[PDB]
Image: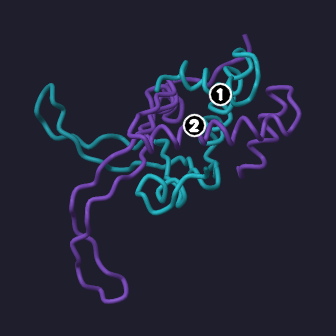
Chain colours: A purple, B cyan
C-alpha cells in the first residue's frame, strides 16, 4: 500500500472528499514528526508509541573503505508497536468486526 | 503527547469537528494495521514504512523459570523511519516553516 492508496481507503472510511483525507494523513504525520522532533513521545493508544531516542557513540563500518569507524551520537525516531497491533498481527486477537 | 492531544491538534489543523479528527486518527490506524495484518506494507513517504516481519527461532529465558527456551515463530509489526523523518530528528534537515 502506497500513500495515495492509503488516502483512497481513508476517503471511503471518512466519507470525506479526497482533499480532506489527504490533509488528514499529512497532518497526522506532521503532528507526530514535530512532537518527536521536540523530544516528546506520541502514544496512539493501541497502535504504538513514536519517540525520539539518542543513540550513543557506537561503531559502524565505512562502506567506501570497509574500515570500522566510531560514529557520533545521533537522535533517531522510533516506533514501538503497542500490544493490540502485535496481538492482531501475531494472530492472538481478531481484527475489529462489524458491530 | 497522548492520543487525545493528537486529536485536539488535528481538529485544529483540519478545521473539523473533534469527532471527525477522531475518525481520522482511528481509521488511519485501522487502515495501516489491517494492511500489515494481511502481510502488505504501508509506505507513507517521508514518514516511514510499516511492515510485517516473521520472527523465527528466537531464544529467550523464561524469567519465571530462568530456563532458556526457543520461542515459537511469530509475525510482528514494524516501522522503518523514513529518510526525511530521520533528517529532521537528526538535525540534518529543518522542518518546513
Q: Is residue A22 left or right of residue A79?
A: right
Q: x%, y% of residue B45?
A: 64, 55
Q: Is residue A22 left or right of residue A71?
A: right
In front here: B88 or B78?
A: B88
User: Residues at marks 1 and 2, common chain?
Assistant: no
Query: In the image, is residue A46 above or below residue A41?
Result: above
Name which residue lies at 49% across and 53% down.
B80
Which chain letter matches label 1? B
The image quadrant of residue B14 is: top right
| Secondary structure found at label 1 | helix
Q: Which mark is residue B32?
A: none
Q: Which mark is residue A31?
A: 2
Please report contact status of discs 1 and 2: CB closer than 8 Å, yes or no: yes
Q: Residue furthest top?
A: A99
Query: In the image, is residue A99 above or below residue B12?
Result: above
Name which residue lies at 72% across and 35% down.
A24
Name which residue lies at 65% across and 28% down.
B10
Q: x%, y% of residue A80?
A: 41, 38
Residue density around tag 1, few if under 14, some if 14–19, many if 20 or more, within 10 Å: many
Q: Which residue is mark 1?
A: B10
Which chain letter matches label 2? A
| Secondary structure found at label 2 | helix
Q: x%, y% of residue A82?
A: 45, 30
Query: In the image, is residue B13 above or below residue A18?
Result: above
Residue density around tag 2, few if under 14, some if 14–19, many if 20 or more, within 10 Å: some
In front here: B45 or B74?
A: B45
Amino acid at each position: 500500500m502506497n500513500k495515495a492508496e492509503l488516502i483512497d481507503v481513508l476517503t471511503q472510511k471518512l466519507g470525506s472528499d479526497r482533499r480532506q483525507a489527504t490533509a488528514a494523513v499529512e497532518n497526522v504525520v506532521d503532528t507526530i514528526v514535530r512532537a518527536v522532533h521536540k523530544g516528546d513521545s506520541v502514544t496512539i493508544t493501541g497502535f504504538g508509541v513514536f519517540e525520539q531516542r539518542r543513540r550513543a557513540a557506537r561503531v559502524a563500518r565505512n562502506p567506501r573503505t570497509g574500515e570500522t569507524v566510531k560514529v557520533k551520537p545521533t537522535s533517531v525516531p522510533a516506533f514501538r508497536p503497542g500490544a493490540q497491533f502485535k496481538a492482531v498481527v501475531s494472530g492472538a486477537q481478531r481484527l475489529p468486526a462489524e458491530g
